[PDB]
Length: 328
DNA sequence: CGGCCTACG
DNA sequence: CGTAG
DNA sequence: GCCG
Ligand SMILES: [Cl-]
Ligand SMILES: [Mg+2]
Ligand SMILES: [Mg+2]
Ligand SMILES: [Mg+2]
Ligand code: NA
Image 1 (cartoon, chains in turn blue, green, cyan, purple):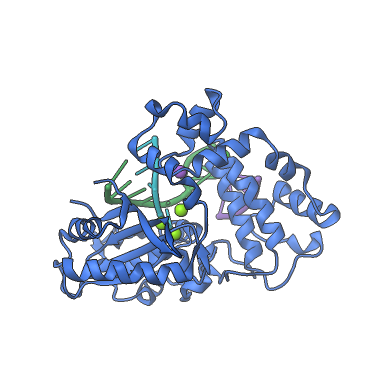
Image 2: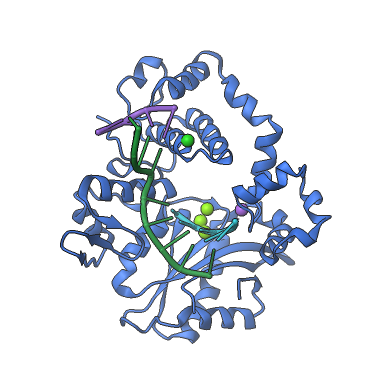
């Protein structure tokens, strides 16, 4: 009664097993910091199964038969049910390795590999990093200078204001181009740590060269605190107005041709785990190769045309899930 | 045991 | 290496 | 870590 892939079941944003899923997610995150992507995936998948259940797990019996629950994830849940805490989870939470890797990887421009190297060198705090700016990229310098603002949640109210300013620049860059809110806010989140936008134009080909024109215009309006500069994804830090001041916010801008827009919308709406699971399902169960540009049949050597996300779910033999049910 | 999503900057 | 969902 |  519980399918094995997250793309085969609705997952709402709020659910009935929040504490259990959060614990499993700590173990997933810690596995990622050690480079164990397989263990990360299993703990993420097990967490997501609990998000999709219709009521709280109250007894270990209720895990029997659920996919992605083996000895380890079951023991975590058992300890939480019996004692309200899991010793392994709490040991990870208080560990210097976990806390420092979490802090470093949260920096824009720093991934697991950089964070791990800094950890092995003995670095532990952001001020440690600030004291040797020679070992930092321009991107990392920006991420470090803006880290405090970037750690503050972006509210839905902030999103609406940002969308209007992006639409103004996009309209001058290319009249008729459109801006669609994606990522977590499209799935119904009330907060986030960034804002994701997808830009297209109804006339195929007109979107070529668009993103540099949009970036130049936002830069000229004084709104860009940082960006990496032909391109189609821009990872920016924007100046967002606040009462009597402003704050830095991460904004991602993506361009797609309208022929690819359903695939880009699907990919950029997420969740991350939902999309990994959907691509895994496509390839392993249907023999089709999915990305944010299209869906390829490698036997016929043809690309599926899609005019909607609904088309893509139908192509893959899956019941449609609206964005609010993709919170795997 | 092999596999674990698949891109772009 | 970083980034994204 | 789990699935097939
Ligand atoms: Cl692993
Ligand atoms: Mg986002
Ligand atoms: Mg983003
Ligand atoms: Mg992210
Ligand atoms: Na980072």
